[PDB]
Each structure stands twice: as structure tokens, then as C-alpha cells.
Amino acid sequence: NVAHGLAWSYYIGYLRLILPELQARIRTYNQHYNNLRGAVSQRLYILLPLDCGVPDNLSMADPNIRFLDKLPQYSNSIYELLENGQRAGTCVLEYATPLQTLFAMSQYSQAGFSREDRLEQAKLFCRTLEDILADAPNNCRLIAYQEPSFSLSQEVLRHLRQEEKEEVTV
Amino acid sequence: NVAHGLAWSYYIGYLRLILPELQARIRTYNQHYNNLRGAVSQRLYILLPLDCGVPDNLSMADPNIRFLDKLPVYSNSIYELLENGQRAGTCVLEYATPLQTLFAMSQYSQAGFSREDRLEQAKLFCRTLEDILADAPNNCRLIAYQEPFSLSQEVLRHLRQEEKEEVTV
Ligand SMILES: Nc1nc2c(ncn2[C@@H]2O[C@@H]3COP(=O)(O)O[C@H]4[C@@H](O)[C@H](n5cnc6c(=O)[nH]c(N)nc65)O[C@@H]4COP(=O)(O)O[C@H]3[C@H]2O)c(=O)[nH]1
Image (tube, rainbow over all chains, first blue to last red; front, side, top):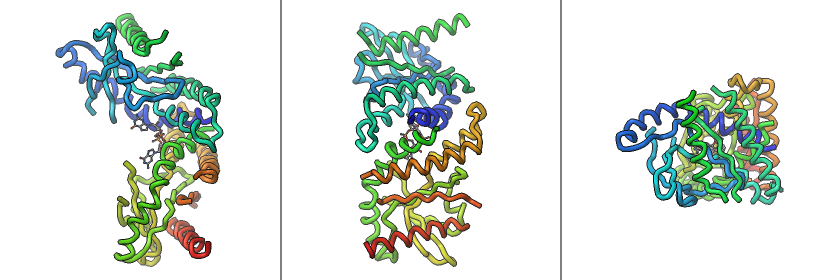
């Protein structure tokens, strides 16, 4: 069951190293984006395409997701989200790199690892990660989505607004 | 059972990316080391301390393993192995980084992951990796060892066994 370990290693070996510093860096940044003319969500957003298809470049993949800026120090990028050519949201967005690992396996013959299997481990990966995140010492949402009526910018824009509702409320 | 996935990811995500190129790079190098004057084993050697203790610097750890050179995104280092202050062998030596992951877990409270567990997953990691390596498309040995024994000697052991197998078959 490879997903169990990929999840842990991604957390222990990556997430728990950037996320502490995260919301500071974003806060530090956000001053100027205010002055220059918007805000950047405080959570890191992670794309979990259950297809395990990670583009080498996210912006070219979805038209409505333009690159905007690199966040100052670990390499993180601020994307703007679009509606009608209008800036509609802005966050730090990333792909869960361990999917690349599940995808390479399903193209590795001696692995005997099928797409059947890969989708299964993908969901498992997503599940187990979420649990890890639950007990961890909130600046980090998981966005699992099965490519089909579906705009990726919209799924992201959805969470994005839900984040701002929770802030002004609680 | 975290070891199953760590193993695979280490292979798919690291090993199978450097090992193809490996033995060329070493061969390319080895000409000069001849002229300058020894040889460098053709396999990449991977340290699996079952304690999961990866020093930030290997040479400082064992006195008998001195750094010698970087081999020309992939960062690899040639070490010389010592006996009596004499150069006794020379290879590219590395620590299996996924152990660091097993060790961090056993110090992460909400993991509930014990040294009991860690040693278990370590061996498992070593086992499963070896199997992966078995069916893979030979420039790469695993050196699992439980600290109690002179590291350099365990490495020197394999090192010579490698040169035996070459001149024979
Ligand atoms: N966006 C992003 N994601 C990151 C970054 N660092 C790690 N990750 C993610 O973390 C996973 C596990 O990392 P690991 O614990 O360091 O565990 C690593 C490590 O043990 C080994 N490894 C990978 N690259 C190197 C390398 O260049 N040198 C050495 N010595 N080992 C490496 O491969 C293991 C797992 O392979 P991966 O497939 O790469 O899987 C990685 C990858 O999905 C990063 O800087 N940015």
C-alpha cells in the first residue's frame, strides 16, 4: 500500500518544513499586494489531481490560472485566479508531487501497478494526508478533484472564498 | 507499513534517475584517477544504518572514510576508504535518505511511531528496496548494518568482492 508512506514522507519531509514559516512570509508579502491591489490567502493550497497528471507548468494547463509572483524565502509561486479576465482570487498553489511517483509506477512494467491501482492509491494518499494534517500543529488545504462541466480555477476559487468567510466570522 | 512507499519513491524518484547515467560518469572520471593513481568502484554504494542515523557529514563520523572528490542536479561524492592511514579503496558512497524520514517519525508524537516500529520499518525498507533493485534494468549495492564494527571495513569488504566478480565474470 504505497500511499501510506508517500503521504508521511511528503509531510515529514516537505510540508512540515515550509508550513511553519508559511503564513508569516505571506503576511510579510501581503502588505504590498494591498498597496499594489489585493490580498493573498493565508493557506497553502495543494492540488491533488487523482489522475496523477502534474503539468510541468500549471498556468498553461488552466487558462484561468495565471502566474503572478514568486513568494520570497524552497520554491513557492503566487497564482491569480480568473473569472472573465478579471482577477478573482490569489493564493499560493502547488501540486502534490508524490502523485508523479504514483504515475511513474503505473508506467513501470516490473511494478505491475495499474491505473486501477493508481487511482486507488491516489485517493488513499489524499485520505491519509488529510488525517496527518488534522493532528498536526491550518495554513494548508487539500484540493482533490477528478478531471471529467469542471473548471479547476472554480474549484480553487470556491475554497478560496470559503476561507475568507471563516476568517471574518470565526 | 510506511516502508513499502518510501522504498518505491526513493527508487522511482531518485535511484532510477541517477543510476542510468552513473557508471559512465565514473568511467569518464576514472581515467584521471588512474593517471592521478587508483580506481573508483563502478557501483553506487548506499549506506542503510538501521539506527536511521544519517550524519550531516559522513567523513567526520567514521575517521577512516575521508572525502576525496565530487563526481562531475545530482550531487555525488567520492570517498576514500582507509586502512592504517593508507588508501584502501574508493567509491561513491551515500546514505539512504529515507531513513531520515523514519527517524523524524519516531520523534513525532502524533505519529505514535516507536523505535520498536522504526527498526522494523527500516529492515522492511531495506528488504523491499533490494527486491525493487533485483528486477530493475548492478551499479548499486545496499549496505545495511546495525551499529553495535568498523564501517569502513564493511564497505571495504563489498568493495573487494566487487573487484573479484569483475575479473572472474
Ligand atoms: N514541491 C516540492 N516537493 C518536494 C520537495 N522536496 C521533497 N518534496 C516531496 O517530498 C517527497 C519526499 O521527500 P523526501 O522525504 O526528502 O525523500 C526523498 C529523498 O529521500 C530522495 N531524494 C530525492 N531527491 C534527492 C536528491 O537530489 N538527493 C538525494 N541524496 N536524495 C534525494 O527521494 C525521496 C523521495 O522522493 P520524491 O519523489 O522527490 O518525493 C518527495 C517529493 O514529493 C521540494 O523541495 N519541493
